[PDB]
Image (cartoon, coloured by chain):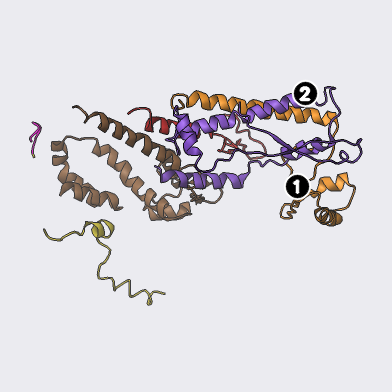
Amino acid sequence: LGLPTEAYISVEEVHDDGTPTSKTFEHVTSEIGAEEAEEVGVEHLLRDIKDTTVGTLSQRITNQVHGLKGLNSKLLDIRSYLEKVATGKLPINHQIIYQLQDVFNLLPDVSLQEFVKAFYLKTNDQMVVV
Amino acid sequence: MPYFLLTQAVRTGNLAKFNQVLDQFGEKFQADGTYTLIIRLRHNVIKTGVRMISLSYSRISLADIAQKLQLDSPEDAEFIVAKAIRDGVIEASINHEKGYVQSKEMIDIYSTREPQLAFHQRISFCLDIHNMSVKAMRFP
Amino acid sequence: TRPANHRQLTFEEIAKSAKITVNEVELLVMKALSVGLVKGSIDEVDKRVHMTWVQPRVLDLQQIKGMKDRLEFWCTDVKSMEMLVEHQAHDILT
Amino acid sequence: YAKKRGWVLGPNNYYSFASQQQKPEDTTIPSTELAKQVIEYARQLEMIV
Amino acid sequence: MSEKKQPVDEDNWDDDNVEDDFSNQLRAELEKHGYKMETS
């Protein structure tokens, strides 16, 4: 699946406020950078599909496919999480409780302003390509 | 000359010159090969007046349009417009209270899903012009 | 209680719930925006107060249940729409 | 017309029911057919050489 | 290139558009157009 490297940070706190003292490994985000003078050593070792830059409309759809295949995977993962976070398994974290709550009632919705604006610029974004 | 004399009297609101031209040029109208002009034009002459008025006036009464259309009957003016709205001459409505005849209200068509549907006609047609013109030429 | 569907609430329901008069709900919501638990707006051409609730809390499992269901409803739509794109555009996916 | 349809005579006044439409359109709902139209373009742009 | 179906078959430069618009609407344009003021 889509799973690159993962990293933590060395932190020493109590736990939160009202829980016993602990370590609580905190996560730091990661990336795989790539400088010059190694990509030529990288590109010459690939030589199998090589996936050239900006694609002719077929690579972009696959980018939206496995861009979304990573979305429902996180949805299924968090679905298995909520089905075991209360079903009687482990002490629920007070942190993660409001950390999930400010996602659902903070997503935008549809209105009249979104409607009249969308067909305004979709007409504009289309007719040139037309 | 005869058809230009024909479309002159039609687009104008005249009848006696129209019948005179019809009486003069009927021999050609039979020699051309259409006879249905005798029945299909008298609908046109009576609806040319109501289409021009409905295009011009945003809100004309029935008692005014009856005297404007030399009709001498303020009772069938509701019936003419009811034939005009039914036949698709103009989209209006009759307020049958004192004789209010309204017209269109809104002019916004742009952000209301008009242009994309015509544009989908333009893309699908011209790529079919394209691919047919592709296959028609690489014969060798 | 209302899940962001018709969060444009009128002054009448707050006056019923908080048992406060009409002439004090506006001083009420000016205080609440100054606190920082919400950043909504106030309209009076319809006299309806808009709510963009931004300050979450702890909740019990009974309100987790519907929250888990609205995750599954969100999950089963995002998955079903993925089946429609993969069905439609497979021939130029490669 | 009173027995078949309405037009019921009351206090010297008929009553005709309204036969108009009341459909509350949103029209961003047919967004699937639009994405269908966008994809079938690039289908027809590509896929034959 | 004839196509085997034939039964039978100057003054202005281009003035149809004005004449299709206005053919006979008192082109002297003075006697009612300039003389409304006696009527009102």
Q: Report the chain shown in brown.
A: B
Q: Amino acid at mark 1?
A: Met
Gap in Å between the C-alphas at discs 2 and 1?
30 Å
Q: Residues within 10 Å of mark 2 (few under 14, many from 20)?
A: few
Tell me the chain of label 1: C
Q: Which residues are magenta?
A: E1-8
Q: Are marks 2 and 1 on the same chain?
A: no
- Indicate the position of residue D33 as horizontal and vertical percent values: 50, 31
| Residue beneath disc 2 | A83
Disc number at residue C51? 1
Q: Secondary structure at mark 1?
A: loop
Residue C79 on the magenta span: no
State the hue of chain D: red
Horizontally, residue B97 falls left or right of residue B65, namely right
| Quadrant of the rendering where the C terminus of chain B is positioned | top left
**Residue at point 41%, 46% (across, down):** A128
